[PDB]
Structure formats: structure tokens, C-alpha cells
Image (cartoon, rainbow, N blue to C red; front, side):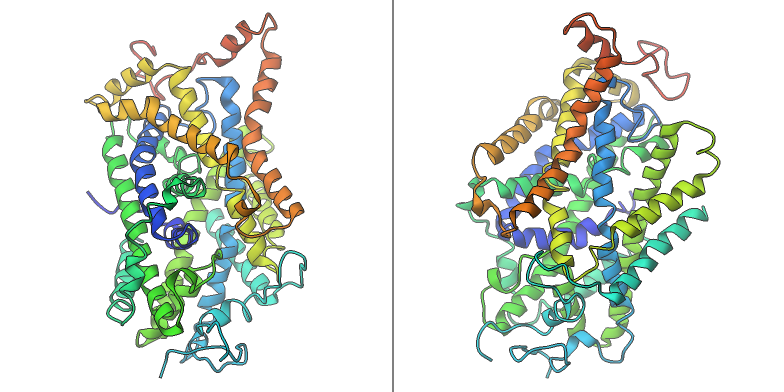
Length: 524
């Protein structure tokens, strides 16, 4: 049809380092399996569910009011996600402003912010370092040893974060595509004909059959397959309201998922190409050429731009594109939260004064993002990526999927699609929804708990209190489900622990098509 949009920050910065962190090519096959049997079939459901009634992340839960806690917990995940994008976005603002010189600062192994073991590509001891790494570590952030020393605050980064939180606010209060693909193609053309790039593509292929029997690989695969698509992420169910009741959500689900996966894999090729040259010209293997840190795009992409002629223009376009991409994501991600919180109160004094709540949500993010921009920035930003976005979105999505088709009913939802789409859901979709995906999610979740929780599960050797804080934050996103369930069970008429459950999970009196002339049969 046309461009499938997508191509967010979860396709240029997240996947390239997640794949390297999960051992490289051992992550691709589980990713394909989890996208085929827990991806697309977890997207058509959300599209149909939103197209049912024109609502957002909240309000749609009129099927089982006791389960409305899923919606409230869904925002909590978005809050922990829509706060650490700007820190990454702010770093992009520190590179756009830095690329204002005839020669790029991260392109010469002679600058004062280097060491004696620095290596070069243009024109001792052990563990040779590429000139790009000794810019992200010793000059941008000045990272300390660990969380043990908080350090001072990087003034340039703190200043750039203010603009990151300001431009979004100004653009929000006042009231495109095919560009990433051409830049990615230009970056792909270079760095592959260079000698040594062949080794960097093989490591992106030939998956290791020995390592596929683990838990971390599939755990990350489920998170990535749900994070990029938008399942329980916010900003996906809400826009389903702005869709015609007779729109082919099946075609959109088929096209968007494939396009997003193709873009992510293409970014994988682009990123892993430079790693081969790094390994070749440094003298180490591909698996240990870099570090398993949160920033790999800022370590691999800049060197590719250096090799290209007339590099400053390319850098200016690339980082400008990245900034616009991040702002485009954050715009919707924050606007949906503001709309939900405004509609939640349902009052008048907090209705016409929407500017104040917009300032309040924006000011809160600015203040709470201060400690991320400091001498211990990498570790704190990286802590909120393992125990904040992983193993919570998948759990919430699985619980929602079970609740829709095992309490409301499997015949009802299947019958409804006939009244929306001409042809019934395919027999593949019926089997995958009912048994396959919930069983896979349950098996992964139980296997990550029964086994594989030793000290070696700590891939990063975090201290006990820090991992305790991360575990506490992880629970908060998922622990909202039973609390609201009990809260609503209190209000229900207290007969016995059999009738209260039925009296609190039945559909409400306004569950049906959003508009009239569509409620004529069962939903009339």
C-alpha cells in the first residue's frame, strides 16, 4: 500500500545492542519464532479490540471491571519507558551540536581525551581500543567505576536535556517518512566493501544450536517482539479509535509487523558491518570487540560516518533524523498519557486548564531525569532497561490475552469479527490465540524462575541494593493487577466467594460498537 511508518528508536538503538548482548546470532532464530507465533497474532487482537470501541488504554476494560487494573499498570510501564528516551535523545542533542567542525571530534586518535592504547584507522600494551570508544567514555559522560560513586553532574549533558524536555512541551502545546531508509542505505553501502566486514555478517547468522536451550535469550526475545510492535506499550490501542469500523485491520497487522521486522534486521546488518572492521583492525574476535553496554549505536555508527567523505554533512543529517524520530515517538507517547490522566478525573477545574497538567507531567520528567545525566549515567540508565521493560510487558499482554478469550468467551470474540471483517479469522489465528501463545509465555516465565536465577544470572554484577531497587520497580508495574481487583471486589455486594467474581467480571451495560447503527443484534 504505502509506507508502514514505524522505524522508531526501538529499531535503531535497542535491537543492535540487544542482539550483541544475547550472544549475537543465537538471538535471531528465537526472535523469528517469537514474532511468528507471539507477534503478528498478538497485534491483530489489539487492533480488533481497539476498533471495537473508540477508546484508549483505559475505558476499553468494560469487559471485566475487576481486570481494569491492567490498564492502570499499563501506564506505569509507559512512565518508566517515557522517561529514559529523552536521556538517549539528549545524548543525540550532544552530538548534533558537536558536529559543527570541519573535522569530526570523534575521528582522530590525537585529541587530549584519549590514552596511550588508543588506535586509529584514518591515514601499545594490550586491548587496543578504537578511537570512537574514547569519546563516549572519557569525554561525554566520564563514567565512574560503578554505582558506588554517584559523581558530579555533566553540565553540557544537563543543559542539553533541558532543550530535550522543552522542545517537546512547546510542540505539544501549540496543537517525514522514507528518509531513514535512504540514510541507512547510504551507511550500508560503505563499510561492507571494506576488508573484514564479511566476518561481521557471519556472526549475525549461523545460530548456535547449543545455546538455544537457555532462558535469557527467549526472555529478551519476548520483550523485544512486544516492545517494538507496541503490545501493552501505549500509543497503539489509543489510535485504534481513529479507525473506521469497516477497516481491514488484518492487512495492517500483516504489513506493519513485517515492515518493522525488516527494518530492524536491516539495522542489524548495518550495525554488525562496522563491528567486523573494528575486530579486523584491532586484533580481537567479534564477540569481544566491544562491551555489552546500553550504547552501541553511539559506538558503532559514528565510525561509519567518519569513513565516508564529506562526513560532517552526513553526521548532521543522521543525528537530526534520530532527534526527529525520538521527538515523534515521545509526542504521541506523552500526549496519550496526558489525555488519559485528564479523562480519568472527569472534573471541570482540571478540564479547561489542560496546560497546567501538561506542564506538570513535563516538569516531573525533567526533575526525575537529573540523576540519569551524571557520572553514573550508563549504569542507572541500563538498570531501567532490564527490570523495567522486560518480563513486565510480556506478562501484562499474556494476562490480557487470557482474560479476553477465557472469561469473556472465545466464541463471542470470534463471532464479532464477522460483523467487522468479511472473512473469519484464519484457522491459524484461532489455534495460536487459544493454546500456543499463552502456553509459550507461561513456559518461558516459569522456566526463568524454577531454574536460572543464580549469581551468574547477574550478567552485570550489580550490587545487592541496586538489584533490590530494580526488582522493586519491576514488581510495581505488574503488582497493580490484584490490588485493583481487591479494591473492586470490596464494592461488589458481599454474598460469597462465588457470586462476587461473576458479579465483577461480566461485561458492563455499554459494551458494544462505539457508534449507533452498529448495535442491532446481540450488542443492541
